[PDB]
Structure formats: C-alpha cells, structure tokens
Length: 37
Image 1 (cartoon, helix red, strand yellow):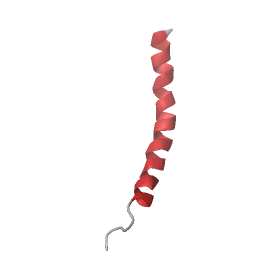
Image 2 (cartoon, one colour):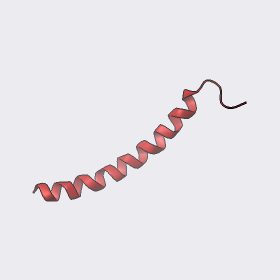
Image 3 (tube, rainbow, N blue to C red):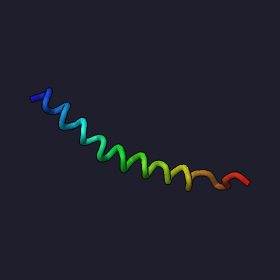
Image 4 (cartoon, rainbow, N blue to C red):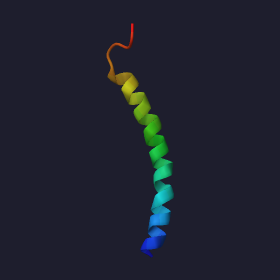
C-alpha cells in the first residue's frame, strides 16, 4: 500500500505545509530587529 501512501502523504503535506508557510512568514517578521526605514 505504498502507492496509496504516497497519495495519502501527498495531501498530508499540503495541510501542514500550508500552515508552515504561513507560520514561517511570521517568523521573518519577528526575525529582523528593524524593518525598512
């Protein structure tokens, strides 16, 4: 059931990957001490 796994894992990323990309986007914001003047 590996072929089925790939299909299952495939969407599993889209769910967490989306939340990740969204979270990381915030990180960069709290990363720089001073934004553009």
